[PDB]
Amino acid sequence: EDAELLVTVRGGRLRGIRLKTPGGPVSAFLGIPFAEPPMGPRRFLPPEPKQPWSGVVDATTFQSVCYQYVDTLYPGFEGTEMWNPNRELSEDCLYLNVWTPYPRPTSPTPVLVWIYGGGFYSGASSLDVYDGRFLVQAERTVLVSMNYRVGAFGFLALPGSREAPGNVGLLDQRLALQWVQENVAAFGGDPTSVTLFGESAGAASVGMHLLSPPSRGLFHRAVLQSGAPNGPWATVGMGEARRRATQLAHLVGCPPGGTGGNDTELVACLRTRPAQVLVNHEWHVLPQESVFRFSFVPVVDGDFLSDTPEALINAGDFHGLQVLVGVVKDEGSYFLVYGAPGFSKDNESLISRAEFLAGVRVGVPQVSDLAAEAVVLHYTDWLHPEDPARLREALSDVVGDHNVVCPVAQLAGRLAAQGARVYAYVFEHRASTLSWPLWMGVPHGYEIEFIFGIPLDPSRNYTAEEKIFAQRLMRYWANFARTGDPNEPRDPKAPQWPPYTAGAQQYVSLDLRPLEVRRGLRAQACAFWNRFLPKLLSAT
Amino acid sequence: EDAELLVTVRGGRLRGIRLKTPGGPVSAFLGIPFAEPPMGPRRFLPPEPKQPWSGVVDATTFQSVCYQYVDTLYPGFEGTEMWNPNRELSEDCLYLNVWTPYPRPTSPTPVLVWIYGGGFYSGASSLDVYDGRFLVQAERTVLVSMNYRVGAFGFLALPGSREAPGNVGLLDQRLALQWVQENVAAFGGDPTSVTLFGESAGAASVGMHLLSPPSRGLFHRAVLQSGAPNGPWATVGMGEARRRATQLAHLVGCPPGGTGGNDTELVACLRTRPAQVLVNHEWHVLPQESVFRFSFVPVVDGDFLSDTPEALINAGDFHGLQVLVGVVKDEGSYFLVYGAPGFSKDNESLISRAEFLAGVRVGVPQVSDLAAEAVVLHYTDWLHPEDPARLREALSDVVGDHNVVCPVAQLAGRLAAQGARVYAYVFEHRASTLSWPLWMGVPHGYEIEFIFGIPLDPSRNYTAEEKIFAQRLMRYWANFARTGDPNEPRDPKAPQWPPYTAGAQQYVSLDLRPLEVRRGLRAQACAFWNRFLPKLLSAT
Ligand SMILES: C=CC[N+](C)(C)c1ccc(CCC(=O)CCc2ccc([N+](C)(C)CC=C)cc2)cc1
Ligand SMILES: C=CC[N+](C)(C)c1ccc(CCC(=O)CCc2ccc([N+](C)(C)CC=C)cc2)cc1
């Protein structure tokens, strides 16, 4: 018996599986329960730690995906199906995975913890693009990844109530962080060197753990890829969260007329519905037509978040913290085919001026007409106010800057100014195997496959340069996880990655070429969103 | 005796004078009266034509400069005193000048009519920089220039009342245009080919005549240099004009204590005051501290202008009209030493961030703080928001765009779209003899000396290339006067000057290097001034 694949934790024993890589094996422990199944009366409730078990839990395959909406916009299309659940759906989904090098480290080893994105309504740790075998083999860190409840099961909130407090999906992540503290040593991992990293809604989750004291003591570095907690999509107010929860209850027959509708009876009725019935109405509760807006997201209750993320970032002391942040080149192009008029993944999407003006109200919903006019002023090329190709890039910039690029830059500058050491990047390589149309450029989410070393998979058709490029990125991420600085420790030959400051605002472009330093994360555009537009909305 | 210096016109006989140029003599008739002296009871009234005289009026020297404020900011300085009056001040100032080639043309010759600027409060046709001997000698055109009343004597208005109708200085200009119609043939000039050209407030004046039906039938082409009638400084409302005229009257003791307030006594009391007393209180009636704002300007009365210039430009059909418009590279730098904090012509004017924010309220007076916030957003480089040099040029752009470059580009686009053939230029040569500091670049008003061929004066220190350059511009301006087209018209190797259209927005740069087409007269900045900022003021 290979004792490598046999490990004991505080709950009991596990058997793992050995994974092959072109350069050696890794030990994987997939599907470890870290919480009691949040079913029945535990729906919408904070997680309870998994009770200890007799025997040996089989940890050889990924467990079930949490109940979530399944994208059907393009059936059979790799670009969308690669994010859909690849396991059976179940509310019994609170399991985590641990990768560790072979042979198991006799040293303590820094631990990377992955939090998947998906707009807080979708995502799973079992997706092939989150496969940690290549990262662990190449850089010999310990990689953990958890499943957390999404959609209504994770973020439905009747604020101020005990039956559905909200943010329980964030607590699921926190519970897996505490599990890493108490058990990662048994896998050769150093619980004093824990680096969180996530993408999209995962990056917002990482940022919200930076701003939550109870979670703050469970990690020491943080990486936020194409996401931030301060953005306009990542949180929601109590009153609007209550309206959406009530809207979902009404759509599924809760409460049954004409019985009372206080918070206890409302959640009690919600707990009797099959989980799929709730999923089938999740998008019906969004107030207006939009892109980059989701129904059940973290709520600002005063509990998990003392105040708004924006407030906590401003009043926050971040000394002793090192953060890696960044975005992709075209953060907004992916979302345009999900509601922007005139857009289609199967043509050039050379939109008209009327479609551009119509899309601005969908990409920037919930704003006054004067605010929309300011957006149109800032993003119109007035020497070419109706060139379709430029209108397409402009709306992509509108959605991208408003939702990702500027909230990130807002966070990056406020962190470096208030004590934190910050590194910033912009991912500019478009995968040679990318299936989305070329007018999308480098879309949201398509740096992940290079961070996780997927090109090293011999069954895939990446090029030789992309494999070398994937090794550079895993080195950057591992160097940062080990030292807090992505630069190679004793290497002066390598082009160096300067920190990001509030004044210089230096970042690097990541692609096949060597590192290239630039300054300003779209400084002129983000000044409009971060500085002027709030003044335009308050003076109304 | 040379008989070509003796010419008879409708009012009587004249003796002129012969002026020398390096390439041949020119016949000049300086000081022809075209109106009765607007003195005594005729102060503030429209001009009356000059009654016929017996004998020979001497026309060998310039007549008196109209009463006006005299700049004292920098005594002894060539940069300011080149614009100050060079003849005695008098209300008896309605005289015009005619230059004509030697020998006098035998066939009708195109006429250029100059209208000096000076914020409607200053200026004279006798200034050395307006000497027409070189333009008339080099291009054998006929040049006329007139004096018109400035300040209160030309533009004090009690709207509605008959004793201070307002715009009498524009009627002075109109009367000089009727004189050119009735008499320029006696000098060899073609009254069917007359081209107006003015600078600053003269360019605005030229625009007002384009929009005035009684004046429109007196010319066929227009050149507007660094000015337009639609700008924020060239016109004033009726209610504001009444308040400025009433405050001036109070500042000089009108009316006497306890006597009535009706408009006849007000003007009657104003007519008893010495002209210098009215001049000494001119800058005291303005509302706020500001640059590029003047007390007595054309009033929108319903008479000379049936509506505002901005409205008349939109509604008018300009088919059959050719327009030459343009600007200098640094339109706003001159005005900063006249009120912007931290500025001085004798240092580098490296202002601070606080001084930039203060200067914006002086450069854009009486706008909302929200409007000023948008101004600062647009002209701050947020990667270098406090570099003193960038703040200096940014404030120069603020004053230049708001007052000159964007009203001109707006007029140029509307003229071309609505039937007129338009040519646009940017003057980018800084005179080698310029006495203003180097940080001012190419200031307001310093293309005039090259248009008028001043470098050809042997008693100056211009370089050889500047003389060649001045001949190119005189050829440009003269070709446009003859043909309505600044091109040769045939070389065709000479680099051509394409018309300005509302779409392509093509203009050329005028300097020592050959002509060069560019696109967009500050397209992005003028979209903020022309398109966005109005909607911001409407929402308040
Ligand atoms: C690609 C990124 C990968 N990761 C990071 C996981 C990722 C990040 C972010 C997202 C959200 C994408 C959307 O905002 C579509 C939202 C949307 C979906 C469906 C609908 N219907 C209306 C139901 C369909 C009709 C059109 C409307 C809106 C997905 C995946
Ligand atoms: C240079 C161009 C030549 N031309 C075209 C004739 C020309 C065009 C435009 C102007 C206006 C210049 C000003 O706006 C000074 C305005 C000003 C003057 C005096 C004052 N005090 C308060 C009295 C002095 C204190 C500062 C304030 C403001 C001048 C000349």
Image: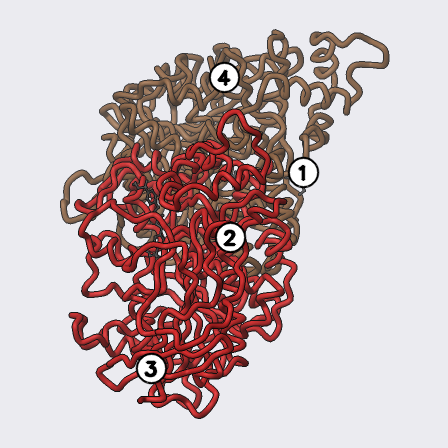
Chain colours: A red, B brown
Q: Residues within 10 Å of mark 3 (few under 14, many from 20)?
A: many
- Can you tell which of label 3 and label 1 is closer to the viewer? 3
Q: Look at mark 3 in the image and give the residue it sits on.
A: A27
Q: CA distance from mark 4 to mark 3?
A: 95 Å
Give the camera-side residue of B351 and B3.
Answer: B351
Q: Are marks 2 and 1 in contact (CB under 8 Å)?
A: no
Quarter holding the C terminus of chain A is: top right
Q: Nearer the viewer, mark 4 or mark 2?
A: 2
Label 4 packing within 10 angstroms: few (<14), some (14-19), many (20+): many
Figure quarter occupied by ligand 2: top right
Whether label 2 lies within 8 Å of ligand 1 gets the answer no
Callout 1: helix, strand or loop? Answer: loop
Task: Give the side of residue B90 with respect to residue B220, left or right.
Answer: right
Give the Cα distance between marks 2 and 1: 69 Å
Label 1 neighbour load within 10 Å: few <14, some 14-19, many 20+: few
Query: Which residue is label 2 attached to?
Result: A42
**Left or right relative to B489: residue A239:** right
Q: Quadrant of the N terminus of chain A?
A: bottom left
Disc on res. B171: 4
Q: Which residue: 44% across, 85% down?
A: A188
Query: CB of mark 3 within 8 Å of CB of mark 2?
Result: no
Q: The disc labelled 1 sits on which kind of residue?
A: Glu
Task: Say whether residue B371 is left or right of residue B532.
Answer: right
Where disc 3 sits, the SS reads strand
Q: Chain of mark 3?
A: A
Residues behind callouts 1 and 4 on a single chain: yes
Residue in view at x 46 percent, y 91 percent: A107
